[PDB]
Image (spheres, coloured by chain):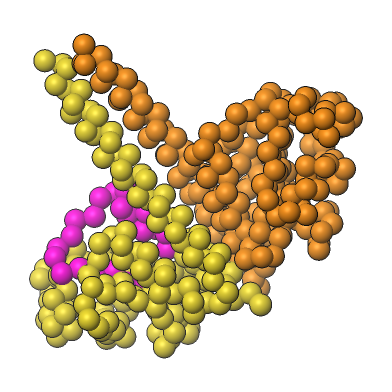
Chain colours: A orange, B yellow
Amino acid sequence: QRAAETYDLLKQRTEELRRANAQMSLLTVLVQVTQASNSLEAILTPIATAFAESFAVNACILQMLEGQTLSTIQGFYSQQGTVNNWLNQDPLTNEAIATGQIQVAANIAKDPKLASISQYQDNGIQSHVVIPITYRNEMLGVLSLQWQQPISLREDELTLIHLSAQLVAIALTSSRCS
Amino acid sequence: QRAAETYDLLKQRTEELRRANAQMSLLTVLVQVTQASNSLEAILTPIATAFAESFAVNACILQMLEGQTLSTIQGFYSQQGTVNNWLNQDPLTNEAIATGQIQVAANIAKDPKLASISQYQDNGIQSHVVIPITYRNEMLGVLSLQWQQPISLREDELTLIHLSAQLVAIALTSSRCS
């Protein structure tokens, strides 16, 4: 009966509601973190951590740029006992820096330009998204999201990444104000 | 039957979903506007306009501060044929500047400190919210929301105002970067 296709539509709304709330929650935390810090360095790990929890990553790295080189300045989170930063050796990151575009590798085994990279293999990284962090046209850094399984991002998750990163860029650019 | 108390809960979820989407939408527009501008002055009206549409105001004013004086620098929106800025003569605004707190006057006729003010009367303003716009502890300006009817803000609407304003403060502080 059409009263069973109402369980199909409440179960649908609630999931959408759940999703929308989780989006709001990430944006809320990013604003809070920005307001509570007093320097750029204090803000980095908290931001990485915020993305890590939102996207259930194995690891997240937020790394600053000087021109088009990765800075030593960075913040990070990992479920592992150590964070292994090999982004300077990463084709995916290198394409992000060059093109100013989000780069999505949903399944490493399939990008042949990525499948044979020792670092992806030894860290067990099977999906990777890297997004430049750009304020106006100034690229301030990159944010890397890493998982040990292949992912399949929804439309809403990609919108959230685009907006998130954009907010983060507003955030970093203000943090440099003494 | 309990199948009629499922229409009561889908009609409930959808409204909550509607609300959450409208929140996301305001935050999205504020980020976009910040990224698309190239100066602080270009950003002001768009931000005021964004709040005006979100909160269905009669008018919105976003006005910069120098120390604790209102600047000439400002942006605004109004349904009226003219924007009448009388915030320098406003006790509500003056309390916001002094206390760094949101000020809510849901029904002017009832604040006796506000009911006899010529400007509230002649503009037909029956409710008024003014929120300082503060980055870290630096108060950059005030944002004023004005209606011709009494309002009754929901919990979610107040959270949105707090976060919004906080984002705007991040936004203005970055805009000053040449």
Which one is in front, A70 or B32? B32
Image coordinates of residue A155 in percent, x first then y, are 51, 38
Which one is in front, A68 or B107? A68
Residue name at image x 67 percent, y 55 percent: A133
Magenta stretch containing residue B162, yes or no?
yes
Residue name at image x 81 percent, y 48 percent: A94
Q: Splitting the image into 4 quarters, where does residue B88 fall?
A: bottom left
Residue name at image x 14 percent, y 63 percent: B150
Which one is in front, B3 or B143? B3
Magenta stretch containing residue A68, yes or no?
no
In the rendered view, does B144 fall on the left or right side of A55? left
Bounds of the magenta segment: B142-165
Residue farthest to the bottom, as pictured: B72
Image coordinates of residue B104 in percent, x first then y, are 26, 64
Image coordinates of residue B31 in percent, x first then y, are 50, 60
Residue name at image x 16 percent, y 16 percent: B2
